[PDB]
Image (cartoon, rainbow over all chains, first blue to last red; front, side):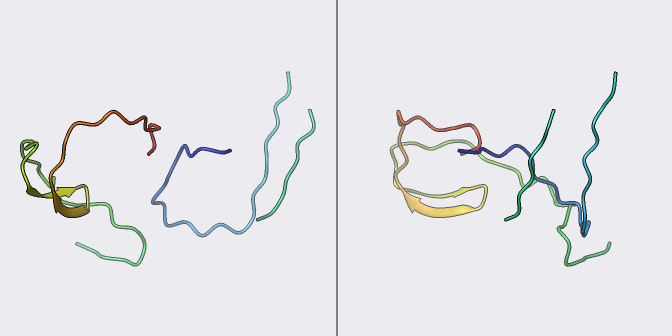
Length: 32
Length: 49
């Protein structure tokens, strides 16, 4: 199961997102 | 002041009152409105719940 952390009353209108790794490890995405 | 279809942010404090138990009372709880007798419980609730 998956339990909430955060709500935000921003007003933004997002269309596309991008991750950000770090340097001195795969990752999965999926849609709803 | 300005109003928008986006969520509002500025409201008055919406002050509270004291607590009344075991007596048939009206009640408002953050928005949930009803009437009844409200008593001390022993259930187990999650923090978000």
